[PDB]
Image 1 (cartoon, protein in one colour):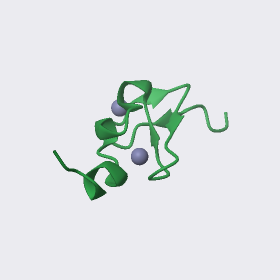
Image 2 (tube, rainbow, N blue to C red; image 1 turned 30 degrees about the vertical axis):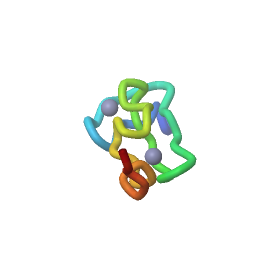
Image 3 (cartoon, rainbow, N blue to C red; image 1 turned 90 degrees about the vertical axis):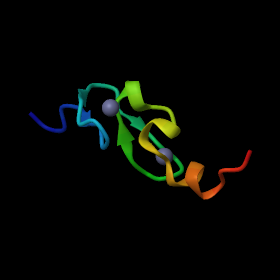
Amino acid sequence: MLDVGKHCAYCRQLDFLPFHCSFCNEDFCSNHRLKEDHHCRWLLEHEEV
Ligand SMILES: [Zn+2]
Ligand SMILES: [Zn+2]
């Protein structure tokens, strides 16, 4: 029993395949794998049009 999956940092969902973001450096369930999903700081930093 060691690191049995990472829980989303937005909805807190225990997933087996945590999506690691190479922009904000955070784990998020597949459902929130997208950037905007977890409100990626990078997306907010550059939001035009
Ligand atoms: Zn999630
Ligand atoms: Zn991100």
